[PDB]
Length: 235
Length: 59
Ligand SMILES: [Ca+2]
Image (cartoon, rainbow over all chains, first blue to last red; front, top):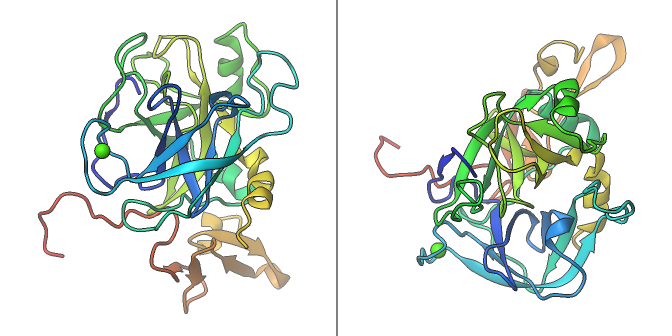
């Protein structure tokens, strides 16, 4: 996250980090005890992945961390239908052993298609992660979060030569300086509805980070909520 | 109706008969006694901070 601030322990208890070929390469959010929702571009078919919930400072030990292995990975069926576009940039991770929910390990709420979209339209959400705090800069040790306003589609569309589909949305500031960035992918874009946070987006991609005239592009969760609930059903 | 302020529903609102309103909440919560607000029905309901952060208040 560029131009954000340190979260306090437990401020975003649904946030998790993903470790693998690279440590802390992406973020993700807790759907329930056994499932994490993240970005598909973070989990190429093959490689082994680990999830750490209740994570705050990547180089320290808070004794709130819960490490789990990923036994199943489900990227959206349409991701990579069209080469190098990032449309449908969402994936689901199933954990080998359930997480123990507590103040530092709590699911994010997921409304239905209609309400997720209404919550997004409130126009202000938070993004978080351990990604770069500077374009091409260092990764963060302490979880970062940043408030970002929703961007009108026409402005979004004109900010880049790349395609922005209806499964995406823009968020960021016209003046730049603040944005999610590399390493933040899979992490959540969340909207607070009277104290209760809802998953409204998934950190997906962008052109460089925090540059004036550019915005963060997010996967629009409203379009995938039925898919998420269907696949993450607890038995 | 749900038209204004989500029909006073803290979480979800659905339009019923005679311009009436039927509220609801997301998993882990329960529609209070006043059929409006949402209350924790489990130890750790989704989307809520329970750490309170820091340590300096009346509590
Ligand atoms: Ca730690």
